[PDB]
Picture 1: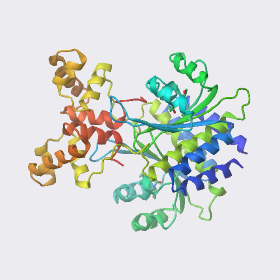
Picture 2: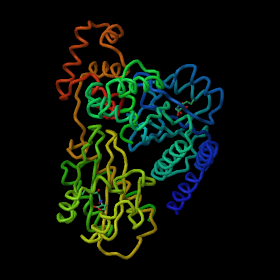
Picture 3: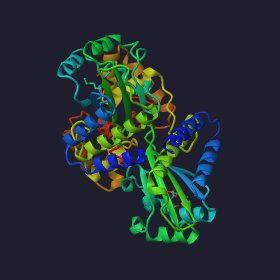
Picture 4: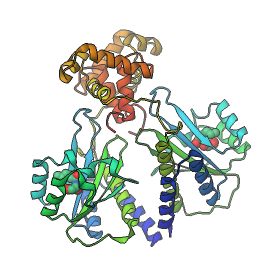
Amino acid sequence: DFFSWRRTMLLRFQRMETAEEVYHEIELQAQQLEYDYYSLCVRHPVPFTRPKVAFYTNYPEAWVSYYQAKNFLAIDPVLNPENFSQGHLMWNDDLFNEAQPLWEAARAHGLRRGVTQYLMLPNRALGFLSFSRCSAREIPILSDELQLKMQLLVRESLMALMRLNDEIVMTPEMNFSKREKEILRWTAEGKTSAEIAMILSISENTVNFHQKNMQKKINAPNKTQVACYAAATGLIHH
Amino acid sequence: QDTDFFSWRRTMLLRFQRMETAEEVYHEIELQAQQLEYDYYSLCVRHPVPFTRPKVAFYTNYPEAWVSYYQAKNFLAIDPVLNPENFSQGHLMWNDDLFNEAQPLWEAARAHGLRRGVTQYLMLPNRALGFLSFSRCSAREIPILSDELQLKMQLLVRESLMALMRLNDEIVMTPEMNFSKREKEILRWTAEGKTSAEIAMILSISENTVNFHQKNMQKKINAPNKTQVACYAAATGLIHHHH
Ligand SMILES: CCCCCC(=O)CC(=O)N[C@H]1CCOC1=O
Ligand SMILES: CCCCCC(=O)CC(=O)N[C@H]1CCOC1=O
């Protein structure tokens, strides 16, 4: 009877044409599980020093504004894979021992209990789904059925959002030609422009143009950043 | 039965996290494969590096005649079972249509006694792609509705490969890069395209030492450039989590 839930959810997400349908479905499923608020967050693998983070939530506008103002993304333990197990995490008082200011601000805004699930996407982006409620001592649930239900919800929603090329999950656009990616693969092996020229039987002049043309559309200083970003997102071995 | 599945997981999770040798993992897969009415299992892993001809390691109890034949005819290069594009929810059932591109492979598999099979796959924290395939000789049918099998296989792919990662098994492990936290920090900056001179200013150290760590970093990995080291680290996710 649970397996039929999995199958319907699988049928639902595969037939979605809109992002609003994805976020709405998450809203419903969260509510079926006695949770009021959902939040879907994605941390991209690049840039390496300040990884891009996009999110979408039905949290109260006041809490979102407060959260961003205090820069809580940078210290939220819910977004730290270390604190997870089997990609699952139940919110508790101890988890926020390092970030109490977050916890108190969240409680002051009406977030008593919550839970988070996470996975890694094909572009190596880290997706986080969080559910939260304002009510204590209600709890629905088996955890096992909870872990497994949420496990599916992160996957199929974010994968759906990728089919639709949504801005929240799609990495900074890097539409390269098959020629450009060949040069990237060899650059990533530590080949010089001269060696890549001989290997591909083209002039070093043509190699450097391609090299510069990729740096153009990404706005990057050298061939080193372009290659590492490509390696980091899996554009090379997808 | 829904309930006795969750407990199956909890034990299997307990099993795999506390296995101490690689043979124990392959052993567990073998029984479950048999418990699931399959004679032959195959666990295959595609590494993310090298970028130009990535290494592929495997372990199976296939008839060796087919193994020798499979490699000899070089079927990996055209095997749809190892192509993530053909999957859905990380799962894939074998049928005559999927092998529309590989006529030599399917009938040859039929000829060696692989009538029916199924494959599950997922991506590991080191960005390696793991594939688990089951196969049987009995020809007949589609088993049990396709939900518990997918889910059983979903777990079996994960925990076996994760167990093998904990054990530093060669089938899953990427080239090890035990760097100092400082050495990894300059790589993050190298991957952002900072010159040794630029990295010096931001970290308050002499340029003599920046060039020093990089060459010292190139030592332990066997590679020429500041570029290849950064790309291998970037490719494996060494540069920002999970390991
Ligand atoms: C305000 C939305 C940005 C945060 C996105 C996210 O997923 C992280 C998260 O929910 N954290 C929870 C934990 C306490 O505060 C929250 O809202
Ligand atoms: C030598 C074996 C390498 C690994 C084989 C593999 O990709 C997994 C697998 O079961 N493939 C199936 C597909 C058809 O023939 C097979 O053997």
